[PDB]
Every structure is written in C-alpha cells, then in structure tokens.
Image: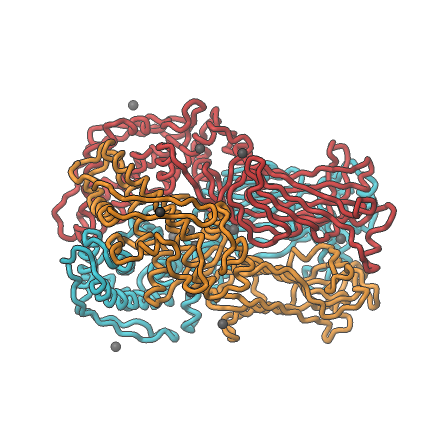
Chain colours: A red, B cyan, C orange
Amino acid sequence: MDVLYSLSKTLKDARDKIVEGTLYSNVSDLIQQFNQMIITMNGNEFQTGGIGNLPIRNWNFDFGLLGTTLLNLDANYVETARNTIDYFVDFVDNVCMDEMVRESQRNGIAPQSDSLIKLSGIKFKRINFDNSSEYIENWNLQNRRQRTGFTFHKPNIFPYSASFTLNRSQPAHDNLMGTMWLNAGSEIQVAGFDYSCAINAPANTQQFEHIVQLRRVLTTATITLLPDAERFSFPRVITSADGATTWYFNPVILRPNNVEIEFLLNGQIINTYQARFGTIIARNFDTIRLSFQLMRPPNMTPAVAALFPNAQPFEHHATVGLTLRIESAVCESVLADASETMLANVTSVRQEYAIPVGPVFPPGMNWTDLITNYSPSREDNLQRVFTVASIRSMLVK
Amino acid sequence: MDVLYSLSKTLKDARDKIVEGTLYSNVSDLIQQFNQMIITMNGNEFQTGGIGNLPIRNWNFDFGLLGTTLLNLDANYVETARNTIDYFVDFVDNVCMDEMVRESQRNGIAPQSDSLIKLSGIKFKRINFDNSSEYIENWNLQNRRQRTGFTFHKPNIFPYSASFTLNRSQPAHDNLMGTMWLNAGSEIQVAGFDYSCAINAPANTQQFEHIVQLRRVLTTATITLLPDAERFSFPRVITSADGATTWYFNPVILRPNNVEIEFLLNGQIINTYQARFGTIIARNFDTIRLSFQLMRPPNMTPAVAALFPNAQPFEHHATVGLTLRIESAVCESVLADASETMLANVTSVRQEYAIPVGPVFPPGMNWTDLITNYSPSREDNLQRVFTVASIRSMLVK
Amino acid sequence: MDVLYSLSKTLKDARDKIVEGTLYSNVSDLIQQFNQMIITMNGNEFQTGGIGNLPIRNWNFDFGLLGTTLLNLDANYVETARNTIDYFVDFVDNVCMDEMVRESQRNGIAPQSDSLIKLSGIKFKRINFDNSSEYIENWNLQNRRQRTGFTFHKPNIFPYSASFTLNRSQPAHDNLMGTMWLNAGSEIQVAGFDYSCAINAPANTQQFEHIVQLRRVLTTATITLLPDAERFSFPRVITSADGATTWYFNPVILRPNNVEIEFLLNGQIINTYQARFGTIIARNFDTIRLSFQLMRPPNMTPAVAALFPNAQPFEHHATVGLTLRIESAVCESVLADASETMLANVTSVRQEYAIPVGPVFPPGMNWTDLITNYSPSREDNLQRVFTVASIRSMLVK
Ligand SMILES: [Ca+2]
Ligand SMILES: [Ca+2]
Ligand SMILES: [Ca+2]
Ligand SMILES: [Ca+2]
Ligand SMILES: [Ca+2]
Ligand SMILES: [Ca+2]
Ligand SMILES: [Ca+2]
Ligand SMILES: [Ca+2]
Ligand SMILES: [Ca+2]
Ligand SMILES: [Ca+2]
Ligand SMILES: [Ca+2]
Ligand SMILES: [Ca+2]
Ligand SMILES: [Ca+2]
Ligand SMILES: [Cl-]
Ligand SMILES: [Zn+2]
C-alpha cells in the first residue's frame, strides 16, 4: 500500500512540478525520487486485470532516467518526462482498479492483486516516499497499532430504517399510540403520536423514546437537534404491522415536552442534553437515546379544544417529534459520508467492469447492507479498498 | 494562467515559510524561486483595472533579491522580505480581479486582461512553479487534451424548476391527476397525485414518472434516495396552468409503489435501482428517471375507507413521492456546489466593481440561467474565471 | 502559537516522510529541521495539566540527533526516529489540551498555559517552520494587522431562535395574522399567516417581513432561497404569547407574492433579489431582510372558494413562506460550521477532563449562547482555542 501510494505521489508531484520554465532547484529532489522509482521498477514486468471485464494488461519497465543538468526546464525536457509519467500513471491506475475490485474473507487488509502483492516485496521498498495523505497516514498508524481517526461530513452511520411501533392499537386503528421514524445516513427523525392526546394518561402526559445503536463509535460529533419531525407531520395512509390493512394518520403537532437526548458509550451516559435545540457536541458515543413526551395542553382555546374530545372518534392525532443530524464527526473506522468519493469510486469501478459478487461485500456494495452487518472482514476489506481508491484519485478522477 | 498561479503559489509559500527563526535550509529552494520571480519581473510595468469601477493601477518592478546567507532567519530578514511580498500580493490580487471581470464569446479560455496576456509571454515562463492545486492541475490536464475531473459536494447541477403537469384535469380542478416537483441544486423532489385514488384505474394503480436531464454528465455520484416528497405533502392553493384561476391540493400520503430509479447515459441505463432507499451510487449519467406508482390500498380500515369514496367529491388527494439528493459527484466541467467559493468570488468581484453585463454571462452571473444554457463559451469562460478565483484565494480571502 | 504549530508540523512531516526505503535526499531538509527542534528543546523541562482532571504531566528533553548518513532509510533508522517522534507527539498533544481548556477575559488571544507561555519565549523561536495551515496563516496575518478570512460550509451564524409574532390576535386566537420562524445554524425558515386570507386587507394583500441580524459579517456567501417554509406548513397547537393557553394553526399554503430579499451591510442594501429562487450570491452583509406577501387569490375554483369565506370562522389559514440556506461563506471571525471539528474538539477536551466553567465561555461551550453574545473576548479566546485544536488535529484525531 505504501509503495503503491508512493508511486502515485511521485507521479502527481512530477506532473505538477516538472513544468516548463521551472528552476531546476525546484525539482532536483523530485528528480532523484523519480529516478529512484525508475531504477527500482526497471526490469520488472507486471500484469493487471482479468477479473470480470477488467482487461488483462501488461506493463514493462525500461525507462531512461530524467536528466539533471538544465538550469530551468525547457519544453522538450517537460515533454520527454511526461512520456514516462503517462505510462506510470496508466500502470498505477490499473494496479489500483485491480486491487479495488478484489476482496478476501481471510486476509482482507492484505494486498489481493498480483501487482500489489509484488509491490509489497522488499525489493520495491526504495520507492517509499512522503506518506502524507489522511488515508495513507491512517493506514500506517493502524499498522503500527496506533490510534487512527477519519473525519467525516455527515457520516453515513445509520443504515436506512423507516418504520413504526404501535404501543397501543386495535383492529380499527382509530386510537393508536406509538412512534414512527426514519434513520438514514447522518439523520434521525422520530415522531411520537397518541390519538387520545393523553386524555386518560397519568399527568395527561405520554412518554416516548427512540434508541439508535451505531455500528461504530463516533467521536467529536457536531450535531443539530431540532424539535418536530417534519417527515411525520403530514396525513398518511400506512400499512398495518401485519400487512393486512391500512391505517390513517392525521397528525397535529405540539411541542415535544421534557426532551432529553443521551449519547451513551457502552451503556454509560457520556453526554446529556435537556431540551437544548440548535448545535450540541457529542464527544464519544455508540448509542443515541431520544426521550420526549406529549403533554395534553392544560389550557385550550375553543379551536384547540375541538380537536381533542373526551371520547372517540379521535380525528386529529396529537404528535410530538425531534430531528437530529450529525453534521461532522470522527470515526476510527472508514465510513461513507456526504463528501468523500471513496465508496462511489470502489462501487463504480466494480460496476463498470462487471465484477462478480464476492464473498465479503454485499451485492452492489450496498451501503445499508454493509453498515448493518459491518463485520471485521468487511471493514478491513473496505479500508484497503478505500485507501486504494484514495491513491488512485491523486492522479485519476 | 500557470504563471499567474505560480506567482500566487510563490507568494503564499514565501509568506508561510519565510518566518522568524526558521533554518535557512527550510527556505533555500524557495528563496531561489522567489529570486527567479523578482529577476523575471524586474524591469516590467503592468497596468490593471479600468473596467467598471475596478481602479486603474500601475505596477512597477524593481526589487532587490532576498539574501541567502542567514543560518536562521531573523526579524529584519523576515520584515524586509514581507515588503516585497505584500507588493507582489497586491499585484497578483489586481491581476486576478481584472481577469475575473472579463469574458469573451470568441476565445473565452484565453487570458482577457492585459496583464495576464502579458504574463503569458515566453519571457515570463521562468516563474512557472509547482502547479499543484486541483484547479491548475485540471487546467493543465485540459490543455494537454487529457481527462479533467472536479469533485463537488452537492453539485449545483439542476437549474431551479418548480412546476406541475396535470395529466387529467377539468375546469373545477376537483379531480386532477399529475405530478409536481422542485429541481434545484443537487436535489429533486417529485410527487404524483391522483384525486380519485386510482378508483377507475387498471389494477387500481396510477403510474407516474419524472425525468431530469442534466446539462453535464456527473460521474462517481453518491446519492440519497428517500420515499415521500415532504415539500408536496401539505395543503396548497395553486395557480392553474393558464393562470386564470386557483386549484386546491389537499394531499394524503401513501408509500410509493414499484419505485424504479434509472441513471441513464445517452439513453442507455447505466444504473437502475428498484425500491432501494438510502444511499446508492450512480457512476456515469446525464439523465435521471424516477418512476413510481400510487396503488389504491386493497384493504382499508374505516378511517381510510372514508377518505376514498367511489364517487366525487374527492376531498383527500392520494399522493406518492420521492426525494433524491446528490451528496457528492465528479464532473468534467466546472460547476457551482455547496462548498466552493468560486462562483461567489467571481460574482462578488463583478458586483463590487459595478462591472457591466457582458456578452457571455447572464446578468448577475445568475446560476440558473447559466446552467440552463451552459454553452461551450460560457463553460470556457467560467473555467478560466473559476481558475483565477482559485489562484486569488491562495492569498486573498 | 507559531512555535507550537511548528512542533506539530515538524512531527507530522517526520511521521510522514521518515519511512523505510526512502531516499535520504527526500528527508535531508526535514532532518535538519527535526534536529534544530531537538537541539532547541534539549535541556528543557515542561509540565502540562492540572486543571480539572487534565493530568499533571512532566516532559524532559534529552534526545540525540537523527543521523544524516543513510542513502535510503532502513527500518532501524525509521524505528529509532519514531521513538523520539512519539514522545514529542505526546508532548504536543498535552500542550494543546492544556491550552484548549483555558480562557482569559483580559488577554484571551495570548498563551494561557505555562508550556505555551514558555514556548513563546525568544529561545524557542528557532523551531518556527512552514506556517502553512489556514488557521496558522490567519493567526499570523491577524498578528501583522492584516485581513483574515475563514471559509465555512454552512456557517453556524444564526443562534437558535424559534418563535412567532402575532400582529393581529384576540383571546380566542381564531383570526390571527403574523409570522413564525426558525433561525438556526445557516438556515432560516419563516412563514407569514393571515387567518382572514386578506379579506379586508388593502388590495387584498397582507405584507410580511422577517429581519435577521448576523453577529458577524459574512462575505462571499452562496445561498439557496426557496419559496415555502415546510416547517410551518403543517397543523400545530401552539402556546399563546403569555403562556396562558394554546392556539390552533391549520395552514394552507399559497405562493409568496412580491418576494424581496435584501442583504444589507450597516443599513445599506448590498444585494437585493426580487422573487429569485435557487442559488444567489450575497457578497458582504451583516443583515438579511426577507419581505413577502400573501395575496388573496383573485380567482378561485369552488374547492378554493370554500376555504376562504367572507365571515368567520376561518378554518383554513392562508400561509406564505420562504426558506434560505447559506451553503458557504467567508467570515473574518472564527465560527462553527458543518464540516470543521474545532468547536467539537475544544468542547470535547473540556468535557472529558471535567474542566470547570470559566469566566469567558458559556457553560458547555454552548454555541447558541456563544454566538448570541459574541464579545471580543470570547472571539479572541475562541480563535486561540480553535487554532490550537487545529494544531493538535495534525497529529491526533
Ligand atoms: Ca502473461
Ligand atoms: Ca473526510
Ligand atoms: Ca390537514
Ligand atoms: Ca460499545
Ligand atoms: Ca479498524
Ligand atoms: Ca498608463
Ligand atoms: Ca470541490
Ligand atoms: Ca449525452
Ligand atoms: Ca470543458
Ligand atoms: Ca513539578
Ligand atoms: Ca472551512
Ligand atoms: Ca455592521
Ligand atoms: Ca477578530
Ligand atoms: Cl450539507
Ligand atoms: Zn454539506
């Protein structure tokens, strides 16, 4: 991985710095590194591809070194350098794709393609150079058994889940009480409804609760918490739990009462916020618990009184809700988020080359399936595959 | 462009590295580059501005070289260096603004200001240095006729469009069937409504479809697809198609049935997803097609039955919807997105200096107008102008 | 600050570049810088911690220099280098945390911990090196009394505010007119309602207005403006202004008429947009003013006519709204946003070590409280603290 990264890094720097007119002193060290790369590769043969429709490609290295005697580089110097650069870029791109389309239940963190396995040999170690990207830094820190951390914008931590739970129901579904929600990506919306508006409830208050267990701990999370669940604030016709019929939801929204959000880690409360809407920080957690209540308004104007009778039929359904969004966070495991193209790169290369479903990843690299059962093997393979996607993106986008 | 970029890059590195106390070995190469820049500029005169209220400014270069003999830089060394740096920064900033406020139907990708045209001369090529930003890398790759790729967070690909299409309507607008939507930025929300709840429809199912044609292909897109269109889930009074009257929309939402999203490229299905909500990958597409149905519930509790009579008046309007958001994607053409300040920089400089409307860009650099008719000339000019904005932002924010 | 940053930068580069196999020429300059750091620190003793539960830690420097004679670095070279690196990383991390948990009403921009105060001494200035991060660049520019600019994605500029204003009301709350809104983070949603649907209003039009005053000027803002306020498009039971009772809101949405958004700076209109939805640029402003109207539909189909009678009771409440979101912007003052982890880092370190509430920051570093009363002292302390968090994140995430 580090050598593959170094190949890419060497090529990116070469492409960027070996430009017409530049002082040789601006590239002297890079030329040394570039030539070290040529010397190390020269004489070797590699073959990539062959899985799915990823073409079999042969690579042969017999390049001359780059000159070291111009004061300022001229166009001919730059152009001959690019001939070599373009070939190596094509090679790196193919090694990356070959590596990205493979997986292993047994040793997922290890190189899977022939070329990466070959590049992991001790004779290729002299190419190693400036491992500075966040992904390679993390790869290296992991390897030395140290603490790794990936920063995400809208971390895709919640597998898609949209459902409800009726805590009080009856065949006619005319006097229900329960919750409905949508957990997806970095967002949670949950509504608690009570068709009776807590008419016979103790203290005329109905308690609700929504618990979400993350598959990985998130640290240093910046979160937006807002009252109301807009998604569950409109009239709906929903399928019954058994799928046998449909019920009617006609919500009228009240402010959630006694809101308490707890960010827990291994059952322990790490952060707790009582009725605080806006931006809050959750520093270390693997579980979110949202508790909120519907309290029947003790004083009601006529228009309100008319919505909540003492007896059925209950035609306006009292609803309270919350919306929680994780804007950014750090995770020790790789994850998909709203900004990085890694998942999309890996998924795209596999799709383009008709790569057959393997033993590790769910069909289509489906994110929900992946995060729902995020096993150690899937994570090691995902990290390997995400790191390669990031090496490839330094040169090919 | 590359020389202008190099000027900015040289100045940014100088400002960052030529700091008090630093080992001379930390800046030796930079000093060489800095001095190459001074030597190349010395003796030249440039003039910027004069368009709109952008002031006419004269620049004269007659600077001494930076010394090369301190072991660790002292405060006096740093301060005399900054006198030169600040002047060059002011110059670069003015060249950038002068370039950003100009456009050309004929040769939009080429330098438009006198200073950039002057800097494109062969005598200024020795300043060229470390072209490493994503924008200049792309500029250079484009120039060598190679594949460029810009990565965006929430790519602003959809011109604002908010409308409806009544597939079945009548003067009273009491039994409509059709769709309404909002395409804007990176998001699409579309709802299909049938006032009759498919009472007389074959298989009691009404089919809907929404097609969106992108003005540019997006690759490696990470997308969130969710059922329901919250934006079209509430009661509305809308203007009729002919503007002569207003109709009433009183939606009740049902789950979209047989959801199928197709990401097509030149008429070919590249990706297709059947009822998959959550995160999905669209690898290469220029068109999105959302197909969904409203199926009359075969089994209805009384409360539901009451909403859907066998005869008019139809007072509750059955509605199904979808929401699609492009979180990130790569595009071969520059675009505005939710994170980059390029469009805002260009638009801001033009607005501040009262730059008159030109022959290429729509008044006010209006994004919707621009993307709606994204001609080759507008793109070449936009890219030139975005690349300059990015050169300027290395020094002036 | 600059020396602390330089320590971190030196360590990050060392960790990244001093890798097995690398050409010595790839690290020669860094080794010089690394050794300059060792020489400068050697002989010194520092102590960190002791506030709250941040442990008291002692640091002693007596390290040998790194060798300068290998052609390509070997594993033993890399491993002995890491022993020194890991210790310095641990030291930098502790200095950062000690600094991040402190504050001062008097001189908030100045170092507060013993270690940072010690590192600000002239004898430690030789460590200074390549101050290139956006935060340190800004710190340095501020210091030279120059223009600083931080770029944010979804700048968290609006303190949480969710409320309403009844311009016409009566005890029964059966014929209200006013506005309700939610200002939070980078978003504003505001709705204007008129239970009478402007039946007795001049020109059958009711005017609305929403003004939001930013605590800091935002420049180069890319904004999404859309008609309708989904958050206020559903039925609600709300508490009365005096808290004595509850009123009923049963909205029916109409298109906002004569929409005018003004971005003002010190009372002056800098940007104005008339009914333009989609993406707009606001280049320099400290205030946003949204003006919109509800115009009674001059022509109504029966279904619409039935919602708006000539006399009470008014059962369907005409509502018009707007949604405005600041996607990105530049601010001269540090702020929390949807991507940076600074606020979360500072807040997290203080929470983890049970740091007592101080004299500057609100309890829990509460963002709303902070931005609501963003005094000069809070900003100077926030900037110091955010810059340290950013120095720490180069090594520890
Ligand atoms: Ca062969
Ligand atoms: Ca990231
Ligand atoms: Ca309703
Ligand atoms: Ca756990
Ligand atoms: Ca792991
Ligand atoms: Ca002149
Ligand atoms: Ca971007
Ligand atoms: Ca096409
Ligand atoms: Ca193009
Ligand atoms: Ca002591
Ligand atoms: Ca930022
Ligand atoms: Ca002001
Ligand atoms: Ca300030
Ligand atoms: Cl976002
Ligand atoms: Zn975002």
Residue A116 in the image, given as x and y percentages of width and height: 32, 29
Q: Quadrant of residue A348?
A: top left
- Residue at 46% over, 57% down: C152
Vertical placement of residue B338 versus C265, above or below: above
Residue B188 in the image, given as x and y percentages of width and height: 57, 50
Vertical placement of residue A213 versus B331, above or below: above
The answer to whether residue C150 shows anywhere in this view is yes
- Residue at 23% over, 40% down: A84
- Residue at 78% over, 41% down: A176
Tell me the quarter of the image containing the N terminus of chain C.
bottom left
Q: How many marks?
A: 0
> In the current view of this chain or complex, which residue is farthest to the left?
A69
Q: Is residue C130 left or right of residue B371?
A: left
Q: Is residue A369 left or right of residue C56?
A: right
Observer-nearest residue: B135 or C110? C110
> In the current view of this chain or complex, which residue is farthest to the right?
A311
Observer-nearest residue: A217 or A5? A217
Q: Quadrant of ligand 6?
A: bottom left
Residue C360 in the image, given as x and y percentages of width and height: 49, 60
Residue A113 in the image, given as x and y percentages of width and height: 35, 27
The answer to whether residue B344 shows anywhere in this view is no
Q: Is residue B30 left or right of residue A286?
A: left
Tell me the quarter of the image containing the C terminus of chain C.
top left
Observer-nearest residue: B152 or A210? A210
Q: Quadrant of residue A172?
A: top right
